[PDB]
Amino acid sequence: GSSGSSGNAVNWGMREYKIYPYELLLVTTRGRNRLPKDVDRTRLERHLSQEEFYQVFGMTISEFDRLALWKRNELKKQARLFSGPSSG
């Protein structure tokens, strides 16, 4: 296939999610999270490089998006990468 370098960023289409480390990309309620001001509490996982995003969830974003809503929303919760929409 056609070769090509990648790394700059997710270059996503819906939005621009900068590449951030899982650590700071965590969602520790009171764990003193270090989430930046350019991360999506709903797409925090998308901010993880295909290299890390896998080391955390155990798969590639491509496969993750192919999972079940509950799974995609369940894993993040276990990886501290989920926030959830205002309940109250």
Image (cartoon, rainbow, N blue to C red):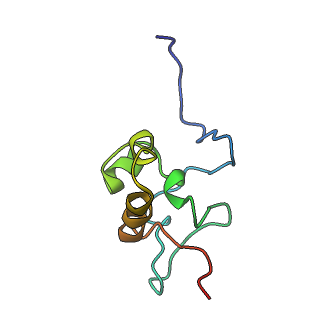
Seen from the viewer's position, the closer of residues 71 and 77 is: 71
61 up-or-down from 85: above or below: above
Q: Residue at x 56, y 58 (%)?
A: 43
Of all residues, the one furthest to the top in this rendering is: 1
The tally of labels here is 0
Q: Is residue 5 left or right of residue 54?
A: right
Q: Residue at x 54, y 36 (%)?
A: 7
Q: Residue at x 62, y 89 (%)?
A: 88
Q: Position of residue 55 (x, y in %)?
A: 32, 51
Q: Position of residue 12 (x, y in %)?
A: 63, 41
3 up-or-down from 23: above or below: above
Q: Is residue 68 left or right of residue 24?
A: left
Seen from the viewer's position, the closer of residues 9 and 63 is: 63
Q: Position of residue 72 (x, y in %)?
A: 42, 58
52 up-or-down from 6: above or below: below
Seen from the viewer's position, the closer of residues 42 and 52 is: 42
* Residue 71 found in image quarter: bottom left
Q: Position of residue 63 (x, y in %)?
A: 39, 42
Q: Residue at x 54, y 60 (%)?
A: 44
